[PDB]
Image (spheres, rainbow, N blue to C red):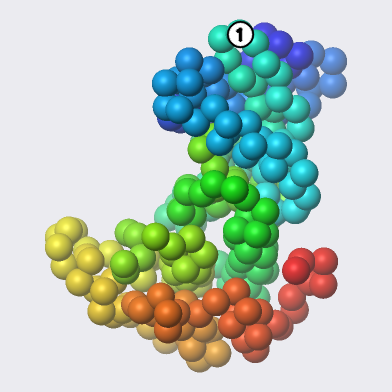
Amino acid sequence: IGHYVLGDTLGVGTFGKVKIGEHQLTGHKVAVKILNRQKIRSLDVVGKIKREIQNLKLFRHPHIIKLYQVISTPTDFFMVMEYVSGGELFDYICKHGRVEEMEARRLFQQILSAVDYCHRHMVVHRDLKPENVLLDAHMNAKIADFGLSNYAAPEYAGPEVDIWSCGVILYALLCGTLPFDDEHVPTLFKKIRGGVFYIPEYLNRSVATLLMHMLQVDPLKRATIKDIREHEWFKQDLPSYLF
Ligand SMILES: CNC(=O)c1ccccc1Oc1nc(Nc2cc(OC)c(OC)c(OC)c2)ncc1Br
């Protein structure tokens, strides 16, 4: 409708819908987050969202969805962002299976560097969830920002909760299944609070020591960004442009 033709609805968020936008001349596809101004005013997060968008504009990380422009109308806010073609990562895992060891390490390094970048450059937060991790045309991980615009850890905390989530995403990459999964809801939290997760034969021992630390119950005893950056398995074939 504006600037870019508006097509099919991708999803429906809290502040409003998110649709696809094709270019009227070139055919370039973008993702438009439509945020309702009245809904923002009713939620008393006017300054919170305005400062979040200002912080997202100065964001420059290739494994995070970039914000191009924000068009303002008296009814809604139009966040023009990059369209990630291949949907969610976890959608690919359950449909295809497990990813190879050196390929899962490639995706993990892209995910962790992005998570760390978000915590040191964002005012407001939502805990990271496998919903945020998306896959592009080049099969690279693209993470959505932890803001108001868009199986929890044991145990307010920000990076500590996300490191545990990175451990869940890491497990799913070289296993195909989740580290903790049970049909019964009370026993699911019991496995998490106990840190009991199955370790497969095909899994390496160096990554097993990293996974054990990342999925630690006590957040004080749990691995930090520096702890993972100093680990042998994570350091192997890690690109210099990150961190
Ligand atoms: C509907 N989109 C969302 O809910 C969404 C959530 C977090 C971050 C960005 C989001 O929207 C975005 N989603 C894409 N790629 C994308 C591609 C999809 O394939 C149709 C897709 O549905 C399978 C999809 O929703 C699952 C997203 N890229 C940028 C944004 Br911006």
User: What SS does tag 1 mark?
Assistant: loop
Q: Is residue 46 above or below residue 92?
A: above
Q: In this figure, which residue is indicated by the disc labeled 1?
A: 74
Residue plotted at (60% across, 58% down): 119
Q: Position of residue 122 (x, y in %)?
A: 62, 50
Q: Is residue 203 visible?
A: no
Q: Residue at x 63, y 55 (%)?
A: 118
Q: Residue at 51%, 18% (x, y): give it.
A: 36
Q: Which quadrant would the C terminus be assigned to in this image?
A: bottom right
Report the side of 35 relative to 120 (left or right): left
Neighbor class of circle 1 (other Cα within 10 Å; few <14, some 14-19, many 20+) is few
In the rendered view of the protein, which quadrant contains the N terminus? Answer: top right
Q: Amino acid at mark 1?
A: Pro
Where residue 186 sits in the image (x, y, percent)?
A: 15, 63
| Residue situated in front as seen by the camera: 142 or 101 | 142
Say if residue 220 shows up in the picture: yes
236 over 72 or under it: above or below: below
Q: Position of residue 187 (x, y in %)?
A: 16, 67
The structure residue drawn at horizontal position 56% and vertical position 36%, both measured from the top left corner, is 48
x and y, in percent, of residue 44 in the image: 45, 28
Single out the residue that lies furthest toward the bottom: 205
> Count of labels shown?
1
